Length: 358
RNA sequence: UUUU
Ligand SMILES: O=c1ccn([C@@H]2O[C@H](COP(=O)(O)O)[C@@H](OP(=O)(O)O)[C@H]2O)c(=O)[nH]1
Ligand SMILES: O=c1ccn([C@@H]2O[C@H](COP(=O)(O)O)[C@@H](OP(=O)(O)O)[C@H]2O)c(=O)[nH]1
Ligand SMILES: [Ca+2]
Image (cartoon, rainbow, N blue to C red; front, side):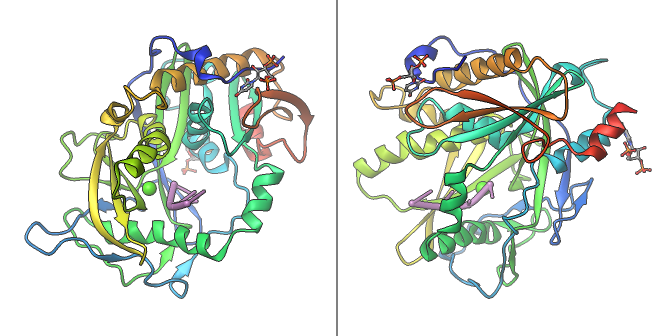
């Protein structure tokens, strides 16, 4: 059996999606070490009201003050599993809640949401059921790995630029000022752990959050969070249209899931400077394509995701942390399944399994 | 997460 992905098959009413609640958080430091606190959280600090406009040099510091995370290290769900293990007897939802949930990274769910419209990059998701709970962990495809290794110099610099933008927009303390004189270390990360539910599928997932805005209408997370992004400066209605049809879909999916209400974009010129900023409220993104014949639809995204979770749940019958049902998908085809045991696909570590078993 |  397989699962189809065409939008037409999921054009029904918007499904139930529980307002996300933050269960906790964790941080990864400069050395990629886990800390069960919010030390890595930064604060939204845009340009001063009276000062000149933005003119952030996103290339400054590249590559001398750049400390990139080692992409060869496949952490999978390890950090999230540590959080779950250290909070297993403090989870809300009542007894047996975790056993009926699906645990994964927000980014994995984002890829599910965009599947009906994605035409360039496919994916693979490893699934294992353990003590009722369904765990989903992405597997880098052979092709994605090859593309990563063949990454052009230009792309490598563009990747730095995205992280550098965050440095110009965030401060270490509330109401503080940004300090671009530092180094860009991508090992550092602040992750929010959230609870939600899509249809009849309870969810426990985590995702990196860029910063907390002290000026946010609602100060309670995740409503107080802000997502930062950079994108090429646009001048023609045609360019904006393409942006609404492809980029906003991804921005929407990513922030809608964790309940992050605003995405702030820095538009960069060909020289690598951000000379303008624009705030995109997550709940207003769809408005840009609501009457677009070539637009995307949140209901299609969510209904497909719900269908995938149902498909995964019914497919993974065996409760075994050493067993993996691999769900593979490439544009133009359905989601297919293959079964595997232990290495290399098995992803639940012994330190997690043994503790949960005992 | 970053990004084309
Ligand atoms: O974007 C897509 C495109 C196709 N499919 C599916 O791939 C199978 C063959 O379709 P086709 O390439 O048109 O010959 C069909 O499902 P099937 O194996 O017959 O249930 C299509 O629905 C899909 O799920 N998403
Ligand atoms: O629901 C929970 C479960 C555990 N803990 C705690 O998390 C730490 C790691 O426990 P563990 O890996 O599961 O053996 C221990 O405290 P510690 O930091 O070693 O004093 C547990 O008591 C906790 O606060 N809530
Ligand atoms: Ca971001």
